[PDB]
Image (cartoon, rainbow, N blue to C red; front, side):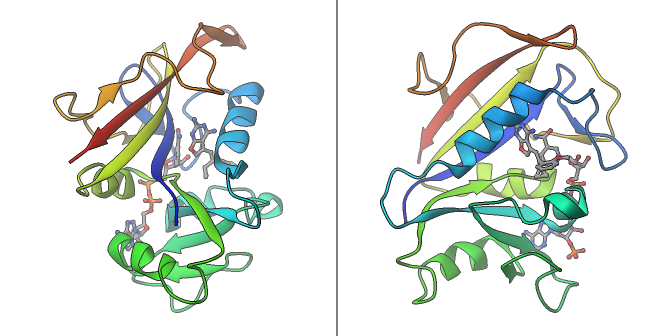
Length: 186
Ligand SMILES: NC(=O)C1=CN([C@@H]2O[C@H](COP(=O)(O)OP(=O)(O)OC[C@H]3O[C@@H](n4cnc5c(N)ncnc54)[C@H](OP(=O)(O)O)[C@@H]3O)[C@@H](O)[C@H]2O)C=CC1
Ligand SMILES: COc1ccccc1/C(=C/c1coc2nc(N)nc(N)c12)C1CC1
């Protein structure tokens, strides 16, 4: 298996969701960037794996489930099998990463992408080893009820450039945002 990564878009007040949707209006090209980053695999004959919590899975409209061209794994202790449209179910992040090493996936998975929500990001961000965060800073406050965990900059280094990531300020629907990549290795 290849690298472990988290990807998120977050407002200035650290918001990532409100009432199971976006705190902000849809940002079409920001979403395109999410699709591109999570779908594109460096390794021939492999797909990337996305790992998400149960609330995040059900926040994807029923017609957009699963995220196409990626292997979709949901984290839940309540569910007894993968939800309709999902491919895998694990009871913990540790278990999901272990699964990625089993016969069924060990040869099929390139990058792994944690795509929410707050508790899955927090566990991933605190997991020892090499990990990158791809963070879109939406540069306005938006009312939220779910928040991105603290990024400890003693460990996470903001990279000065990254291939395939635009470095200038973006704007859609009057909302400015910018892309960042952070890397730790501990
Ligand atoms: N980039 C962005 O702005 C993103 C925004 N979002 C937003 O965030 C919100 C949803 O996120 P959030 O509320 O945090 O919820 P989660 O997706 O993380 O879902 C929480 C549920 O998933 C399960 N879960 C989470 N972590 C684990 C774990 N380690 N092991 C097993 N099960 C786990 C639990 O389910 P159970 O009870 O079944 O055990 C828990 O109740 C929405 O607003 C959505 O729009 C989501 C992703 C990205
Ligand atoms: C309601 O949100 C969606 C609806 C349909 C399909 C995918 C999504 C998702 C989006 C983003 C997750 O991390 C993200 N990170 C970035 N920078 N942007 C995003 N847009 C997501 C998350 C998985 C539920």
